[PDB]
Image (spheres, coloured by chain):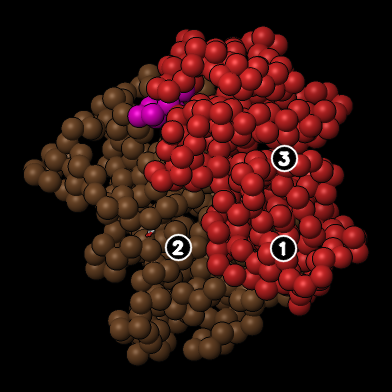
Chain colours: A brown, B red
Amino acid sequence: GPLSLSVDAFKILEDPKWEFPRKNLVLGKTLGEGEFGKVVKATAFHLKGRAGYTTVAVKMLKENASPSELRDLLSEFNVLKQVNHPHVIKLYGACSQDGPLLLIVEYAKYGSLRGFLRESRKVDERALTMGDLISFAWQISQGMQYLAEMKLVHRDLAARNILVAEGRKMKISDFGLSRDVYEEDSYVKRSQGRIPVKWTAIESLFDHIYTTQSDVWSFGVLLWEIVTLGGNPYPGIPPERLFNLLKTGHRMERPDNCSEEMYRLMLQCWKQEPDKRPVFADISKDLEKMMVKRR
Amino acid sequence: GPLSLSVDAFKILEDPKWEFPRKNLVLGKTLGEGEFGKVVKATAFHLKGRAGYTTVAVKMLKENASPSELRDLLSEFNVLKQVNHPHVIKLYGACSQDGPLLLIVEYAKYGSLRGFLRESRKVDERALTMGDLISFAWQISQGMQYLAEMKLVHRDLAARNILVAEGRKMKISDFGLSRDVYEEDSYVKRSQGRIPVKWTAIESLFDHIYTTQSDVWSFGVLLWEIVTLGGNPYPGIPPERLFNLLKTGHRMERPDNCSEEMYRLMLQCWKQEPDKRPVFADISKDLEKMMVKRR
Ligand SMILES: Nc1ncnc2c1ncn2[C@@H]1O[C@H](CO)[C@@H](O)[C@H]1O
Ligand SMILES: Nc1ncnc2c1ncn2[C@@H]1O[C@H](CO)[C@@H](O)[C@H]1O
C-alpha cells in the first residue's frame, strides 16, 4: 500500500545530504512524547560541517509504533527538508539504515512554549512583560506567513508545538500532520483528524477542510494560550461539547490581563467564515502595532 | 460530518438502560492510558441493581482529545453494549450528560495480561505453569470465537489489551478499533491503521484488509507474548523493517520454553495466506489437546 511504497522508496534514496552516520550520534534523556513518537536530547559528531559535537534533538518512533505513526514521522521529514526560516525548527539530518529511523533536528534550549509560559509569570519565577508575549506571537505569525506562502498548512498549531530556542526565539515545530496545499488551497481528510478538538477550526471539525485560514483559527487559540501564560483552552468544557458550542456562535471569553485589541484579534481569528479571518500578514501587522503602541 | 452526527445523536438517546447518574460515580487513581483515552479505577453506587458500591473501571478522553479519539471512545461503547461473554470485558453503563463522556466497565483485578505475565515466572514472584499459559490462551481463543461468530473483528488483539480478572479469568478488552464485518466478512481502511505494526497481519499491513483471519495472526503474536511471559515481539527490530521481513517470509523464531506443537500453532497463525491460518474454533481445539496431553 501507500506506506510500504514510501518506506521502500525511502530506503532507496539514502540521500547523502540528509543521511548522517548512526555511529556519530549519541542519544540521551527523553525530552518527551509528541504526536507520533518520542523526542530525546542527543549529540552529533561532525554534523553538517560543524567541528566537534553539536547538541541536537532526535525524533523517533515510540514502542509499538503503528503505520499511522510511521507515516507521520516520514511526513515530518518530508516537510522539514523543504523549509527554512528563522522561526521554523531546523532539520539537520536523518539515520535511515542499520537501525530505527531517526530525525535529527535543531535543539531548542527552553523546550515547548507551553512549558516556558507555565514556568513564568507577568511583570512562576521568570518575569515576562506583555511586550515579550506580543513578541512571541509575532515571531510565530512571521513563521506561519512563511509556511502559508510555501503553500503548507500546519494543522497542529498550539503552544505545546512551538519551541523556545536560545535568545527566546520561537520555533514552529511538529510537522507530522502538516500538508501540501499548493494545488487546491485546501487539505481535506475523509477520516477523523488527530488534532486536539479545542485547537481545531469549526469548518475543520465539522467538514474536515483544512486551509491557512483554519491555521489562523488555531493561531487564535495559541494567542489565548500565550496571553494566559499557558492556560488550558475552553477550561472545564468537554471536547465533545465543542461541536454545539462553536456552531451556536460561542467563543472563549476575554481572559484576564488581556487588552481589548488583543481579544479583538483572537475573536477575528475565530470568525465562523474563514474568509473573514485575517491572514498571517494581517496578524503580524496587528501585533507590531500593539508593540509600538504600549511603548 | 460523521462525528458531529454521532455525538448529537448520542446526546439524543440518553438510553436509561446504559445511562448512569454521574453523582453515583466516584473516580480514583489512573490505571493507565489506552488507545484513545485514560482508564481510572472508580466506584459506583447502586449500579445495575447491585446494592451499595461496586468497584469499576472508567474509560474517558485524555487531555486534548482529538476527533479520532472521541470517535474511538464512542465506537468502543457501541460495540460493548452488543457483546456478552465470560471472556469479554463487561460494560455496565455510561455518563453522557452534565460532564465528560465516561464509560463504566468491569474492573479486572490483576490489570493487563502483559503486566500480569511480566510480574511472574515459570515453575518474577508469581509461579505460572505451562498449563496456566495454555489455559489463558484458550480462554482468549474462546472469547475470540464468540466475537468472530458475532461478525466482529477486534483488530487490536495483544497482551496489553487482555485483562486478568478475579480467578485469573481473561477478559478481551479495548474495543475502540473493533469493526462490524457482517456484510462483507472484511473491514477495509483507506488511511493508515493505528494498530501497532508488530501485531498486524501481513495483508492488513500492506493492503489494509482486516478479517477474522487477520485477528488470528494477532492471536499468534499474543500466543508468543504469553509463552515468553510478556516478551516484546520481533525484539530489536524496527517496525518499519517488518514490511520487507514479512513479505520475504520471515517470522519470529521458536522462543525458549516452547514446545514444537505450540510453535507450530504460532506459525500457522502467521501463514501468509489468510485462508491457510486456522479459525478460532481450530485454535481452541489445538490448545485443549495440548492441555490434556501434558497431564
Ligand atoms: N527540537 C526540540 N528541542 C527540544 N525539545 C523538543 C524538541 N522537539 C520536541 N521537544 C520536546 O519534546 C516533548 C514532546 O514533543 C516536549 O517537551 C517538547 O518541548
Ligand atoms: N477494566 C479494567 N480494569 C482494570 N484495569 C484496566 C481496565 N481497562 C484498562 N485497564 C488498564 O488501564 C491501562 C491502560 O489500558 C492498562 O494498565 C490496563 O491494564
* Disc 1 CB within 8 Å of nearest ligand 2 atom: no
Q: Is residue B244 above or below residue A119?
A: above
Residue at horizontal 60%, vertical 16%? B293
Q: Which segment is the magenta one?
A: B234-242
Residue B248 placement (x, y as % from top left):
47, 10
Residue at horizontal 25%, vertical 26%? A16
In 3D space, how far apart are the residues under numbered discs 3 and 1 (Cα atoms)? 22 Å
Q: Quadrant of residue B239?
A: top left
Quadrant in the picture for the C terminus of chain A: bottom left
**Residue marked by disc 3:** B87
- Mark 1 or mark 3, which is nearer the start of the sequence? 3
| Mark in front: 2 vs 3 | 3
Residue A15 placement (x, y as % from top left):
30, 26
Q: Is residue B262 above or below residue B38?
A: above
Local packing at callout 2 (Cα closer than 10 Å; few below 14, some 14-19, many 20+) is many
Local packing at callout 3 (Cα closer than 10 Å; few below 14, some 14-19, many 20+) is many
The amino acid at mark 1 is Leu
**Residue marked by disc 1:** B102
The amino acid at mark 3 is His
Q: Is residue A181 magenta?
A: no
